[PDB]
Image 1 (cartoon, helix red, strand yellow):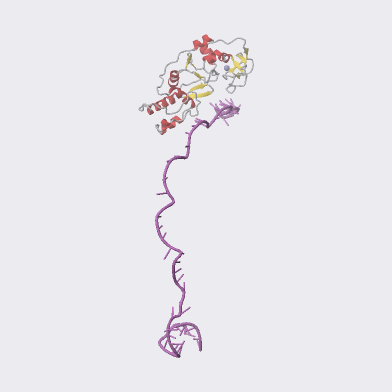
Image 2 (spheres, rainbow, N blue to C red):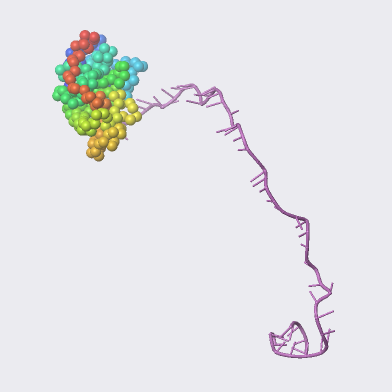
Length: 240
RNA sequence: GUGAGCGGCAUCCAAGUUACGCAUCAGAUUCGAGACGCGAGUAUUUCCCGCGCGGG
Ligand SMILES: [Zn+2]
């Protein structure tokens, strides 16, 4: 899998819609997934409407949308892929905290896309870049493009465990917000400020925003136990 | 063509109501406007201070 639109024909196996124009000009990328639209490929002109708030994330100004993206842009597809992890095998739901911990500590090997909506409904799937290697996971949370490294997540979890192994009252070394919205997101808490060594503080201050967002779900007083998410592509196909 | 470019934390809200610086406490005890200015002592030079003259 190479493009976000590749999930349609590879895990949803949906044939293209009808009434679609056929490109008969010089190739140009899809305005959504940057996929080339060569001669003979089925496309459709852009008709996003006045409620499209993702003009900044458009891959190109070609005003053309491939059929895979047209399938992806359906309301049933948007709602189904709000908290979805699309691997080669199928589509899983990472909405639960345990699923997030499993994904960010024991990721699947194959290429996969990670989606997470920050609101009721958002355009995600055609914006998420593919994660080619599980060591450098690219996560699209709403409008933010996050890079999550599972090794850094594990190291931060170990740092917290060493910090709070003895004290009965568990305290978060770093202030984290699940929405990545608080003005104190990523700042060191007091307990971590005078209970962590210089190296651990330096490591905590030098984590990517995506790692802070992930730890905002995985790092708590009682760490969630990782579990495999349930397959969802059947539900999405049935509702489509 | 710096994962760039583009993007109002913004709108609305009474610190207010009620409350005695007040009650009590000698500026008192002693003592004169009534006393204080020379009619006090001889005759012509003696030791001396400034130097004929000032002066013990
Ligand atoms: Zn596309």
